[PDB]
Amino acid sequence: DVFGPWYLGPIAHPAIGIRIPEIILTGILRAYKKRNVAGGLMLSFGRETAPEWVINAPPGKYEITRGHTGTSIRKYMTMAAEAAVKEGLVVEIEADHLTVAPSAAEAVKRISGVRTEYRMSEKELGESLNYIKAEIDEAVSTGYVNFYTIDTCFLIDYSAEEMSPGELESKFSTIFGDGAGDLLKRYVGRQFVYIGERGIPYCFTFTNEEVMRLALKYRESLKATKTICDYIKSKMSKPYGIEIAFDETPSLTKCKDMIFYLRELWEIGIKPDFIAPNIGFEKRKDYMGDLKVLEERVDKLAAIARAFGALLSIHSGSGSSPYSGKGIGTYEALLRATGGKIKYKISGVYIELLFELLASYPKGSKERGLYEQIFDDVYQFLKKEVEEEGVLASPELELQLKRYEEDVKNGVREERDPRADFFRYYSFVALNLRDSSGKRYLREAIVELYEEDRKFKERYDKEVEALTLRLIDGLKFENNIINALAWIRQF
Image 1 (cartoon, rainbow, N blue to C red):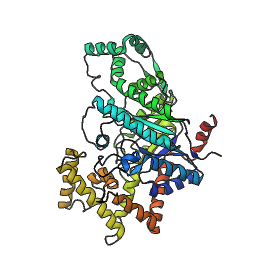
Image 2 (cartoon, helix red, strand yellow):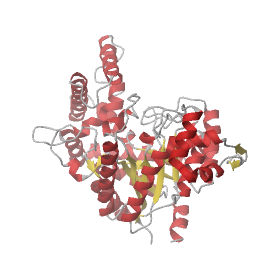
Image 3 (cartoon, helix red, strand yellow):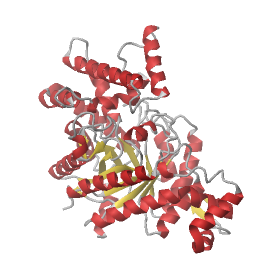
């Protein structure tokens, strides 16, 4: 009998963030069990979660954004694994977004519409890598981690695209030396053909200049990915897979970039199970583009990933609301483009669901009181961050704050509207705000509400399950366990 944490391989499945595992696991696992789904359970290593020593640190040691959920790597992995064992379910315990970054605040700005063009020093790279190793050590020590997503997008060198031919050629020769001709031969003068679900074969060719630019653009990303992957390999006594996070970039992923990235990974001995392109999905929003162009682009990118034994992994999966999925027609286009062979990720939407549920209670009730406390404390914390130029401060946040103030002043929006932009984007700090004795008072009060109030527990579990079911049914993950079992059987 196969149950508990298993590495599932390159097979279609949902993978779901569990920011407060105490209150979210029941409804997710109900849905997984009901639709005979093998699903992932995760938190992002650069933002949502952190090692115990970060989580348990005194107030102010670490930026609010680092492990902002209050949930350690040991905690989510252990609770998820042991919950799955108890339900007799197969799950994948995933370490999402192992992120090279100078800070969690920067990694957050990156997905909240905030331009920073920060550039990392060599010391920062070193400490970022050592933080990632420490995160990995904690995951490994649980005995339950099956899968890792690597995010080195911060290291992409966009200057390579603009270098003059003279500079390009000179830099290329210098760094690649006697390997230069070999690297060019992998690509130049070859017709690459990838056939997508539609049956359309797509042709790609490469010039020398293109390969030179791609090579310089991605060299540091590739090296760090190698270093991270080697360390994971040194520590893991069970099988695992790798996902490449390629999605937190300023523009859409280009087909040639992905062909090149996957192939260069393969040359150094790395075969990801999944790759996560930027296809124009944005956090906290339904898909805002042409569905036909979306389908065309995903059909191409999936064809390419397929030839490297990988599936697409779709990040920023949640939409404008807990009930909106990712927009009408969006799932269908993805399904046609991938034939259902797809990984799909959601996480923050469950807390947005929580807060809006609390907000829908009447003033006078303790649930609504809790909501109002959350919203007020978040608002005042962010105000203070802008005034004191704290780590989350930016003109974008300042504007959103003003816009909520004037919206209320002009009776366009109601006070404490959970749909206010600043709140949708930054409500997450609620779970890491601390009281005078160093406790995450808001995260604790949420958990107490859930654990001691049966009516609230029941209603949240029902909403959590329902949300998970909308995803599962929308993306046809029902019975996906079959292919997972077919992967596991080969070992």
